Image (spheres, grey):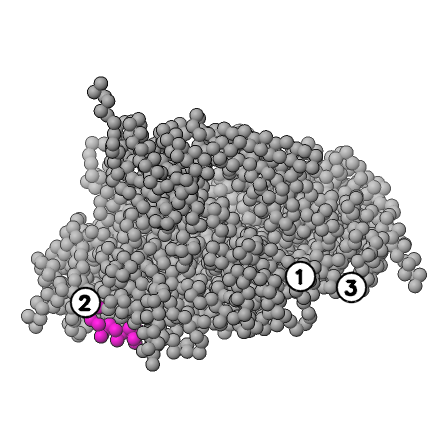
Amino acid sequence: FRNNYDGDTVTFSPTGRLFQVEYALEAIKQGSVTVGLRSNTHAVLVALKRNADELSSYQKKIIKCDEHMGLSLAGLAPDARVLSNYLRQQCNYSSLVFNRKLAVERAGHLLCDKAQKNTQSYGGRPYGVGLLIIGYDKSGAHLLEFQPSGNVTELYGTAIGARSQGAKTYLERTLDTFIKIDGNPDELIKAGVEAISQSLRDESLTVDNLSIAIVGKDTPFTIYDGEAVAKYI
Amino acid sequence: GTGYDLSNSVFSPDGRNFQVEYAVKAVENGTTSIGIKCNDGVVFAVEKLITSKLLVPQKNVKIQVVDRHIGCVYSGLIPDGRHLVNRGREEAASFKKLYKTPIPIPAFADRLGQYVQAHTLYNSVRPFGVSTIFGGVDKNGAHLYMLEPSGSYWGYKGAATGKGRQSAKAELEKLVDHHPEGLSAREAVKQAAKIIYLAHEDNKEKDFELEISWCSLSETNGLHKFVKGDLLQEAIDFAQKEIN
Amino acid sequence: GSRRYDSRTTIFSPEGRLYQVEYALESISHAGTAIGIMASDGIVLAAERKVTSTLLEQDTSTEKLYKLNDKIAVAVAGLTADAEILINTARIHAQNYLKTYNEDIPVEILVRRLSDIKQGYTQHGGLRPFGVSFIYAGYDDRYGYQLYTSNPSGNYTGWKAISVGANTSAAQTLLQMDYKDDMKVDDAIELALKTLSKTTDSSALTYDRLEFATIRKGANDGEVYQKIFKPQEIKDILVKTGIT
Amino acid sequence: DRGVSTFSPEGRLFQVEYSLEAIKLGSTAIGIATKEGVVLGVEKRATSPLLESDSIEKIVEIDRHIGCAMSGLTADARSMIEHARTAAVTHNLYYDEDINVESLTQSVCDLALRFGEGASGEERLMSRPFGVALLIAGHDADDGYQLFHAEPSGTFYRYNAKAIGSGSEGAQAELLNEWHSSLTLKEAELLVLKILKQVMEEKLDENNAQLSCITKQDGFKIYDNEKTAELIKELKEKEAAE
Amino acid sequence: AGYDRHITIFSPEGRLYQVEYAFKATNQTNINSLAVRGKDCTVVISQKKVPDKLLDPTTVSYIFCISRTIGMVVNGPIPDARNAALRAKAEAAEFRYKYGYDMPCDVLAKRMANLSQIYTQRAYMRPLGVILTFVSVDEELGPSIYKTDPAGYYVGYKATATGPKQQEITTNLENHFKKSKIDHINEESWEKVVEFAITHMIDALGTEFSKNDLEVGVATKDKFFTLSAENIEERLVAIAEQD
Amino acid sequence: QFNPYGDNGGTILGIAGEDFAVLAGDTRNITDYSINSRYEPKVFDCGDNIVMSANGFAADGDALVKRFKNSVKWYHFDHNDKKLSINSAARNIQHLLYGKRFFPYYVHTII
Amino acid sequence: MTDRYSFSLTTFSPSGKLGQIDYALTAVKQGVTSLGIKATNGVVIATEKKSSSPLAMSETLSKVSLLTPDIGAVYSGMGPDYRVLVDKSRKVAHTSYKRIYGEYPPTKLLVSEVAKIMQEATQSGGVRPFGVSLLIAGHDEFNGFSLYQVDPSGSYFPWKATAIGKGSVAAKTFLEKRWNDELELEDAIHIALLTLKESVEGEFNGDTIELAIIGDENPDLLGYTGIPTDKGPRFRKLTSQEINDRLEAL
Amino acid sequence: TQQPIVTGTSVISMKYDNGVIIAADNLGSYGSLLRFNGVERLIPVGDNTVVGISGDISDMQHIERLLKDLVTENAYDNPLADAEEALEPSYIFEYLATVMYQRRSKMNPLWNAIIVAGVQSNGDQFLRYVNLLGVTYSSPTLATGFGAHMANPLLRKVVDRESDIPKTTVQVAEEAIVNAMRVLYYRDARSSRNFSLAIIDKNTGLTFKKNLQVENMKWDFAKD
Amino acid sequence: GYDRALSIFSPDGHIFQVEYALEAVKRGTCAVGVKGKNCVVLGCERRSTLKLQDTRITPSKVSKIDSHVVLSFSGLNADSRILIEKARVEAQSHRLTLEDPVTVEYLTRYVAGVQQRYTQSGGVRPFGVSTLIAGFDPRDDEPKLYQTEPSGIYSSWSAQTIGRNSKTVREFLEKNYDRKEPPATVEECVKLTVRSLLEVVQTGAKNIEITVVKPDSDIVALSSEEINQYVTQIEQEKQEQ
Ligand SMILES: [Cl-]
Ligand SMILES: [Mg+2]
């Protein structure tokens, strides 16, 4: 069965599946967990960074796309660089041409259509990364989830990577609480740390291990690393 | 021998293209969507599965508009459907640029039809993993279509595709028989909510969110619009009443 | 996609051989034998017509000996159609040299160019090699009378006497046993026919199965003559050398 | 067959994982970062004694403040150095300043995944991944002395110390215990020379191993054989000392 | 060694299985068609089957108006049919523009046949799974039927039939042209040539026809057009007042 | 024939103190003998503590300022939020301008 | 999309056979018999019209084709492949010759350009060879009357007479008996009709036989008068009647 | 490089306490021939923006289609197309300003002067000019062609600086625009009595007035 | 058009096309270079499968790139021609732009960079060739000798051999070449080259060709008699024991 229909992305299986895409989806789960959640006033990214040795640095998980939008990654970083690059240029074009901040909904639609082109043409390969895109636009706080299948979804909260089901279930339970943390960035981040720590097992999140990013009403997208995330451990 | 199903443009010994047949499996696996042709327009409805309480209500819109007068809904691989609507939009713009008039639905139908068929001519592409239900109002009345991964399309009185297609087709067939004079746009909207609720028993384990749109000459001035607020609620209640 | 149906004509074997070049050389080994012999005062080209008939017009016929210039010629062994593609580019290379320099092309420069084209088909492009082996017989004022050989690999070499196609092993032994450096053209004519007469898989060696060419100077001219033998002349020489 | 940018069912690219195997078959290379500079060391590994060792160039200058060591298919590195050099000089032509070490590394890694048979993205014409890993050592004003590991997977890590090639898993475990944040440059030199000595099949002298460093003051310098000789002598004396 | 059955390359028997399998696609629709020539007209009858009640009958047709003068009936799946139709229309419009006269029936046929022959020799293109029957009243040749297949073959017909029950219809017509000794229906009005076509389709298939079971096309000097349900019902009423 | 250049007048002035700098400019935009605006800003904060004016043809000046502000944004993205030193901004603008050597931006620019 | 078949589909096998050329020649063998006979003052080319249905009009399919006013072609094998070869043969006679020298190419040179087109189908990316063998008959001022055979390989050979397709082995034997260098064009037509009779199962009349000659100039087929140097085409397709007259003396 | 053929004269405009007024005559001139008389040179886009175009009318009609194409495109996958994510005057302007500058830079201009007049979503007045060179400027008063020379001087006696805008009512502004249209008919040799006028108020929305005429003209003094 | 990846990684981390290209070199006739104190000498064996050759015209194994640099090789003869041409063109281009002949290292680096490119470019197979490149830098007297292999790796050798039975003749040179004391004369450097081939060639008067390169573009090819004399003297060394 599977072996015959997984050679390339241009081939359907007899059950109507795209195996090269389902293998790309597997690159995400093998990746280090990350979490997004929002209120009406702010959206947060919390990510667990992963080091090779105790001599190596922890690989950066959060990328800024514009002053009002950015994303966390899980899977191949070199693909996350390609898509975040593309998204930076869409945010850029909107500004220079229409003097208009790109809508977070429209960022989703553009990523989706770029992902899709790799999964219907011979010689291409699907992207091997998942992204949690957060922004504040003219219709407030937004959190997107991107799969390399092309599927983009708008959620109040979610997590992707290894053991990501722990944080996702916690959020699913906390929903009524964190959706109402409006005009308090500190308490939203604390709620997102508690979420990610539901996906721990190995270790306990430390100062040079935890990465957090926030965007909101009067907060441009900014990344907190090291000593800056001390007060949240 | 065999291997007739590994390469897209290839004919089996019985004259079939297995790669197109396998794309149909991706569609059948999809969510249930329907079109209903009323006496001056068309109604589109679609089942949206709620994975979790985390999906924002109303916010992940599936029904897409082409030009200002055409509606499209699809079942199967959603990004494939999007790729086709982008082609739809380029095609309608191209036509309007040259001929001034907005594209007639039959003209627009064949434009999609020829593109999708092009994607069964070569082993270097994959067939579309969607069945598309689309139409609207032109110079000489309302038109409903459905378009398979093979490129096959026809006009329909009603159409349905994906998970719940047998429940829907059954319910559509009854309407065609019980209303020979025609259905109104107000009625067709209610009737469309009902057919999506009844066809959601093939998926009854997960909760769901109803989405409806319409193009009526009298009710929306021959323009595609979404059903919202009171008229959406009236239609939800009409189905929640009749499911019991 | 297409990958499935690619023979990959330009790869190495584990032994570091070129499959397609090896199999093309195999093809050529079945082809009518061709012999080149260089003397002090000229060159001889003889070739065995593979397959004939009472009805094949031999006066209008040319399948092995081709003029590239007024000083250069080739004996072919292998696919004729392949040879004619290479022959035509070589005829043009010679005319480009003459236009650029106002001198007739040196024989090695023409040979190297053809050989480099064949090499190309070996290393990129993914097309089958030219199933052809050439004997070149030329004259220029640098190296005088020259004899070269080229094969599907793009490899060329120079000879005093050589054979290509069928029975080269047998032919090369016989040439090497009765060839002396101070030979005259008339002696090379006789040697060339004897060698063919002994390697032939056919009953006898008649005029209607041979192509014959010579490149002799004149003491009463000082210029070089290419004489492609007409059927009657091949019949005459065939008696004179004692094969009737 | 099967495509060159195909995914395994585990979620890994075939051609990148096989490449990582080629890099284990390579000569050893060790980098050690300190607050007094970064040190780069390599096994020369001559295949015969008739080979003129000092024609083995596995440590190269990128700019005055950036050098790199290689391990794997070293011919694959030539076009990666030519791109780094061009990047660093081009950066200086446009901004009248030295390129950051991290940006130079990012630039080299952006090449690594440009392989395919016509992959729906840009114009990645290059049949296969590179078969070589790079250590990239440098200094800049912003983040100081830095060592980076640059793989054919397009990811780069920052290491306090790192070993790549045949002796790697062994040598890394040695660097794990030995490295501390207050190492001097002289300590770093001996520590490289020592770990090479352990993992090399040959006996280490000034002809089958090469040292280099990069310091803010003098920039990137390959040590000639006479200076490395006197650090080998110095190593031997300290190891006999207990 | 088994891939000579997947692309248009020769088998060891000198055969192109992809072409042979493309001909098999032609019958997938289970529709029979026949063309006949009048004194100054040409008529194409095709079966019309509408299984689904949710279908719009009006939008279900395998007859296409290529140009003012040329009509085309297709035996094969509708997607390939519509591909062939659009190309034939495009070609028809470009011929007029470049050469200043209406593309003739037989020349259009040759051009679509040359296009089919190319899919028969180039590997990246599959043949179309359709048989194209072209009809006009040519201003030079007169009433004309020209048919092309996935092999790139084409020829002129006195009359012709296509579909699963091709042979029943063919031998019916064959017998009529042995009896009449001529090579056209000797009839002045197209109305009585359409009645001839429908009559012989009933006797060859052994089936009756309602007004929605048939689809009719007529070529006259300077116009090709299709009949409505209502134009056919008139036609069914006349054959009924004779049997 | 179509003239791609025009002249919007105005004047700008840059003076350097020991621990500060100023860049000044009138707010008047003109065409021939007509006034277009009495308040059209011409001196811009580009971020990284660099101010810029490109006086002359407004359309060529607004283009250059736009391309430079964007050059600052992409420097931050490409070089880990590094600050663009004035000497570096200058060299970057030399390349922006020389880019159109054979269809120049009709501006005199100060930073 | 985009032809990604940039590689040969005809490669050498370990034996040194080119599978697709061998298989194409098999397709030629299955095809209907055609032949050609050279006389002192003309050439004749002949084939059977094998109608695919008695409802088809065999006049609307030519197996014999005019390439230039002095050159004609016939085939055995796949008819569609012949049709597009005739299109390309007519056009190369203009682009490569007439639009340069202002005369029609001689027979041997037009044959060469067809051979070249067929050779390319044997080596180019993403094509199969042509499944036909052509017989090309022609006159030119400096070479006189000639008859050539062209095989899927792109190899061509000059013939006093020959046959191709189904019964070609038998037919070649019957021509080797009857042929001489002193045949008049009438005697060659006669022999062609006899030879083709051994190949035809059913009806053998001028409605089932397609025959043409390269003969004298036909000034009545030129379509204008006044210019003496122009004497009109040497190619003439014989009528259904002209065949039937010579079958009553068979 | 082109030369304009059918042309439209002055576009005039100013701001007031609660929005903006724009006006332009209904004439397409063909050199010295006053050829076409029904021509609308005010393009409404959504219900918060008008675009007034002078110069070549073939180029105007093309710019009119670019704006309908922009409206269609913005509604695509945009469930807030009639709310928070509707087109703003500033979005429409910047789009035109970009196209204009690109076309001059390819030596193939759109031979026009354009004035975008609207109210932004936040209640702010928008008024900005762009022309075939890609030159752009704001002012409390803006006019094209002749309007520059004669309308600005009259309209500036009502709003000379920004501080004057909240002191100016709709009635006062509207009268000023109507009088400027008369003065232009007196003195511009390529102008028409008939004109369209648009008000965009941040309360009453968009008011578009067609088939207006210059009234209360003084010709009586001519007889002496 | 044709961009198929022919050189790819196998699971154990090898590039089979590159590996197999070396096997073509192993099959090729032997080539050897030894560098003297003040010269470099290039030796190559000639086959004997067929022998009826014209030695006037047959392309010789040692090629001049510039007046001061030579290239010999082992592998596919036809592949050799493509490398030699590219190098000769790079030689004239270098002189045109830098106003100075190539160094031997530069010319080598260029040839090795080309050989490498053919190992990661779509649609091509690697060169089935290894090269010795020998000469004198401009206005330098210190001899240079370099080796390239299909992978694209290069390095400099006191002495080296490549091609069939190169294992044997390397083993000879490893225990007959003193780095302390390089062959001080042209004569004794040539003799050490012939001696090395005689291990593999098996009685070859006409089956050995020698080229001597000296400083300042002084290059010459020995004749059959000049080499035959060297063979004679080396066989008397043996028999005098
Ligand atoms: Cl055609
Ligand atoms: Mg094909």
Q: Is residue I27 magenta?
A: no
The subunit letter for the residue under badge 3 reads: D
- The disc placed on residue E214 is 2
Where residue G182 appears, as percent x and y from the top left, is: 30, 47
Residue at the far front in the pictured view: H167
Give the left or right position of residue I224, taking residue B228 as reference. right
**Residue that numbered label 1 is attached to:** A229
Q: What span is in magenta? A: B168-182
Kindly check if marks 3 and 1 are in contact, taking CB atoms under 8 A apart as contact.
Answer: no
Q: Element type at marker 1? A: helix
Q: Element type at marker 3? A: helix
Residue drawn at x 16%, y 58% is E218
Residue H205 seen anywhere in this rendered image of the structure: yes
Kindly check if marks 3 and 2 are in contact, taking CB atoms under 8 A apart as contact.
Answer: no
Residue drawn at x 44%, y 43% is H94
Q: Is residue B171 magenta?
A: yes
Q: Nearer the viewer, residue B158 or A206?
A: A206
**Residue that numbered label 3 is attached to:** D176
- The disc placed on residue B231 is none
Residue at the far left in the pictured view: E241
